[PDB]
Length: 107
Ligand SMILES: C=C[C@H]1CN(Cc2ccccn2)C(=O)[C@@H]2CCC[C@H]1N2S(=O)(=O)c1cc(Cl)cc(Cl)c1
Image (cartoon, rainbow, N blue to C red; front, top):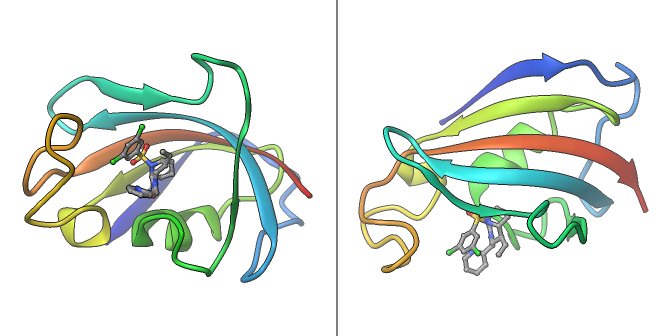
């Protein structure tokens, strides 16, 4: 599954739901490894629409637990990320992922 651990608090009121456009900054890391990607490298925020399965399941379930303004750590098991296959060259097989996510706004 996905574990959500808060780093810094959001508004405690505005939590995204299916069909909303969520704007975030994030860093993605392998558990027991290093960073593999971040939004903040280019500084252009990452945008996605919740509940359209355009991001991994752990994001779908974990970002839905975040409110606007919040920064949280998401720990995502392989079955909620990229499973047995991964994405060779960036995410290995059977990888647990850790993300530092900051939910900026709904757009
Ligand atoms: C590239 C940005 C996305 C990619 N996706 C969607 C997705 C789309 C197609 C293939 C793999 N993943 C995702 O679901 C998640 C979570 C949202 C932020 C980013 N990733 S990510 O795990 O950091 C990532 C980032 C990058 Cl550069 C490549 C991969 Cl294969 C995965």
